[PDB]
Amino acid sequence: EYKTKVSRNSNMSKLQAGYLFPEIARRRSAHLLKYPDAQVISLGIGDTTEPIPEVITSAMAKKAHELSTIEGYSGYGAEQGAKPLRAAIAKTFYGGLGIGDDDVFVSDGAKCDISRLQVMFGSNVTIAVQDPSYPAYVDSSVIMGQTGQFNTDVQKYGNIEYMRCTPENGFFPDLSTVGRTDIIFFCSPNNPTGAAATREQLTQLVEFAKKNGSIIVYDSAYAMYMSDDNPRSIFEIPGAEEVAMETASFSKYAGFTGVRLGWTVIPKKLLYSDGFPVAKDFNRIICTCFNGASNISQAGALACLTPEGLEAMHKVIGFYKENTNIIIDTFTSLGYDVYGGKNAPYVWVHFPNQSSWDVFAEILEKTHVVTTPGSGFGPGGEGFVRVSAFGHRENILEACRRFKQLYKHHHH
Amino acid sequence: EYKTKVSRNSNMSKLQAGYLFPEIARRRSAHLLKYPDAQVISLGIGDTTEPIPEVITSAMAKKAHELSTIEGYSGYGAEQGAKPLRAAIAKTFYGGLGIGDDDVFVSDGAKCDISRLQVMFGSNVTIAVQDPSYPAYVDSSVIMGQTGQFNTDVQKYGNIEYMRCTPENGFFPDLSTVGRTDIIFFCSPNNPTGAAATREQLTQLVEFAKKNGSIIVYDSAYAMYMSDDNPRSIFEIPGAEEVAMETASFSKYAGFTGVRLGWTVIPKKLLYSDGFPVAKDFNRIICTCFNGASNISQAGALACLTPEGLEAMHKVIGFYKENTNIIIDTFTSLGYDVYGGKNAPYVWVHFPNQSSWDVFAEILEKTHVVTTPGSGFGPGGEGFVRVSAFGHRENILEACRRFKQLYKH
């Protein structure tokens, strides 16, 4: 067989396996070969299951129809996004926090923004992540060349600062034990633990970043699920504008998981060590490596940020919050320690003295329910299982009755 | 003022200025400040102007409505793209060329694919590009750290192999003078020259890559504008499957510039030096760094690849090709050497002994038409100007009558 003379990217070689969620998909397929008549319920990947509100899809269809008229047709948008959408985002989510429309960059999703920010930061930065955290932060770091090899003894890539978040520290890092890095990826409410940082904790985080001269990348993707009285944006902390940016998405709010629209906010006071504004490099990246969110997706997002859109999103979020309460009540009834669920549409269940992949496998085998093993979100990680609350009501109720059957003899 | 201690990415510092088209749009904005009532006609960035056919928009609207029903709602799609769409692409554009549905990766656009491919290749590869060429290839290379600084004496970034394409060589490089690199970015029909490589030239390119152990990244974004009888896909050349991948987009065929859908084709027999298949690393990038093309955009694309869709696209393409002819006849009547326009919806006009940025500025100032200066596409480059054919018929006619008035005399 012919082979080229080009070397495989050594950063790709550093990666341990496939992305977590593809590997789950594999095990689910293998399960269905074993049990062809199983009624599988997926509470794994956090994918929304209910229809997008009519107020939102009507706007998208209307925009689509307009594209076939002389008067309504539009080509390329500004790659930062439509001005009225940037304005609406700035007002709706950041009004009072000193964010201008020009600080908002509209994307096709937070996942893709993470990787574009990582292209911008480059191979020479060091990163810190919550441990556990959404696996894309770590994986994007490895791909960009920011790390060493994976150490199988500690289950960590070298040169990443994994800030451990545990029942014993209230799922917020002990910052006095955290080494300096250039970047700090910080998610609140956190995926997978569900923990939302308090104002006092975020204040300490900003103070930490300011003293270390770090940039915080704040992921507020689940902030609309907040029930506790905690900040929804990092920009609520005075000083955040000198050390933080924020990334977010409509995915979990509007059912936009397949529609594709997010944003990143980068303040004017966020500067590199030479005084260069970070937002100017992001703008370069966005103009050269991206061609903007879909015009139809942008019109949907614009429809969301209206009285009727906002009411529709509250109703949807409210439905998934009650799904999460059912799940919480289920595991608590069975005697497990269950974390999260209060401020986020998933629960973080403690299965001490077992490996999370084993618990994942046992739940899948016995109940035909897919969950997510905690070690998929990093070594801190082990052994919790994340259970998603997204699903039709009857599917959630049925999953929970299957859990009850599986776990009835465990406690006490 | 407070500054962090994070060091600016030194690859960002390398970049000589803003991206080409934003910098033009700035000059356009300054012009409208100076003359608020100027009737500006834009023939700069190749943005489509005609409405998307109803067959396509009706499919997208229907998909949008379906997302509001229990039965029609869908969340995350496969990051690689809906299997029926990957199948439609494989069959429609590559049927008979040995391309399987699993070799197709559906994206939100070719510009974004070039960047994802460059993340995949990483910092340690060297690149060759046509000179002139579409600026994203070079800029993505600089961003990924594949280059040195910009050299102002030659107008080139260090460590990039600029393959010279000229009227004199038929806009195809003398491959015996081209140094070995890992990657060869090749556009056919080329943007900005309009030149479409013949089957023999492409055969030479494949033979060149094979003996050098290079990967060709073939950009066929304008291939549907082909008039000459030349290959539309690199995979028409036997042996391309061992050395080449292809990228393309719906933007220019369906007016999708704002809708967002393209694809990359990576063949099973394309392997890194250690035997590892390239498509496998691409798939890993796509699962980690991307969440899939919009479901509505995929529905629109699926409707394009039907008899009705293909008919609509043929009609729109034919319209823009007539526009191009008008532009060619205009500049030829004025005594300019004009290249391209046969196989692409833009014309490459030679303005001898003059700076293309100066020409761009004169045209804008005097006629209120925006063009693209050739130096924007690299040192080879100077001083040509690219004129796009995308526009309502009346605006193309008006723009041409403005050029005639300015130059005729």
Image: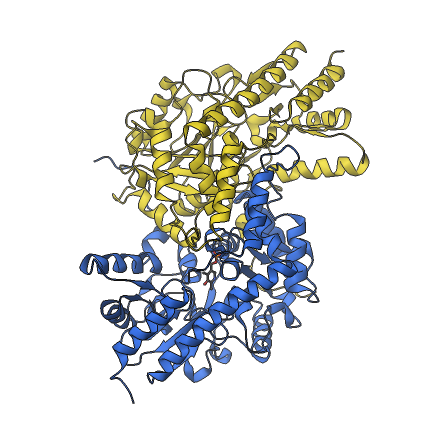
Chain colours: A blue, B yellow
x and y percent of residue B331 in the render? 65, 14
Q: Position of residue B267 (x, y in %)?
A: 31, 36
- Percent x, y of residue A217: 54, 63
Quadrant containing the N terminus of chain A is top left
Residue at the (64%, 37%) spot, across then down:
A72
Q: Is residue A272 visible?
A: no
Q: In front: B129, or B408?
A: B408
Q: Establish if B273 lies above or below A223.
A: above
Residue at 41% x, 53% y is B71
Q: Quadrant of residue A2?
A: top left
On screen, residue B56 versus residue B390, left or right, reads left
Quarter the C terminus of chain A occupies: bottom left
Does B394 appear above or below A15? Answer: above
Res A155 quadrant in image = bottom left
Residue B143 percent coordinates (x, y) = 51, 46
Q: Is residue A60 left or right of residue A375?
A: right
**Farthest residue toward the bottom?**
A412
Regarding residue B313, the answer to whether it shows in the image is yes
